[PDB]
Image 1 (tube, helix red, strand yellow):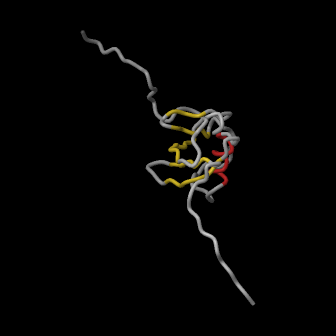
Image 2 (tube, rainbow, N blue to C red):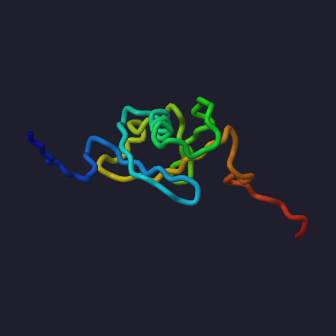
Image 3 (tube, rainbow, N blue to C red):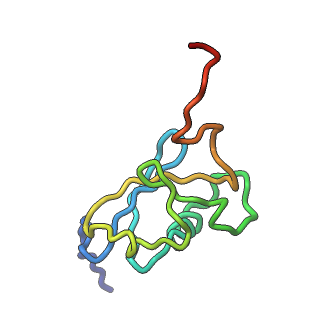
Length: 116
């Protein structure tokens, strides 16, 4: 018989965009995506990956599964391409599952305390 094994390389190309999928608390992993792929493909990919790390598992919507970037949220129709993101790089993004907001607190909101 015979056997062979040659091949090793750990570097992101300039045609793909490395994305960092983070979860609650922490735990993250480097991924790859195209500029023609939309948050869907990504969010989807993530879902497809891993066996199951979330009780809930019986939905299908880009809303519930929204991708966060730099704190903000990316649209489901948005695509790395439209994000004119730099190739051969690593982006940081957060993921969550909720048809609504995460916490009761929205940016750009001033309060008026009863006092002068």
